[PDB]
Each structure stands twice: as structure tokens, then as C-alpha cells.
Length: 66
DNA sequence: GTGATCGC
DNA sequence: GTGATCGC
Image 1 (tube, rainbow, N blue to C red):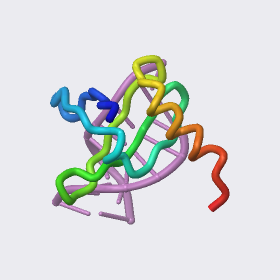
Image 2 (tube, helix red, strand yellow):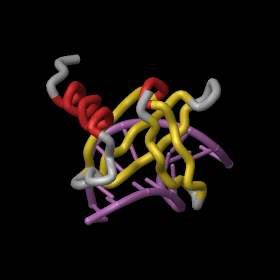
Image 3 (cartoon, rainbow, N blue to C red):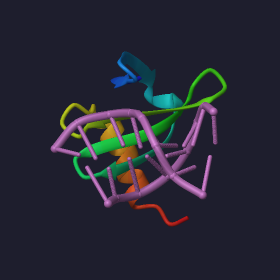
Image 4 (cartoon, chains in turn blue, brown, orange):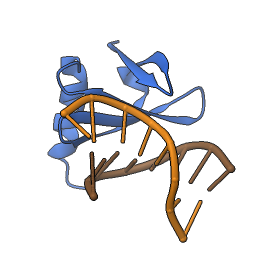
């Protein structure tokens, strides 16, 4: 789908938006957890460098009642 | 610090 | 129990 390129521990990796489990904002930072080959990894990008698909995911989280 | 979590 | 981690 949409791939998010992000740096974690120097590593300039990426993840498919379909692997992202959880999304949340901390200011202008968009943070998330994703299913890493059967594991949970973490990641974060600036809201500016976020593809619209990641901001839609966040939009869904923010309007959620759970 | 912050939200949220992993890794220890 | 909580340090690093991510962008600011």
C-alpha cells in the first residue's frame, strides 16, 4: 500500500501502512507501532513528512471510542 | 516533557 | 521500574 520511510536507531527503514497497528500524535510528531515480521516495532515521522494515508489512520484513531 | 511502547 | 526512542 503506502510505505512510510522513517529512521529508528539510525536505521532509515520503512513499513507498509497495512502493518501499522497503532497511531497517535505527540505535537507535530506522528508515532506508531507496527507488526515487524511477527514482532512490534515502533516508529515516528514529522506530521509534514507523513503520507495522507498515515494521517487518515490517525484521524480514525482520534475519532474512535474504545 | 510529550504518548506509547519496547527492551531490559 | 523505567530509559531510550521518535520530532518538536
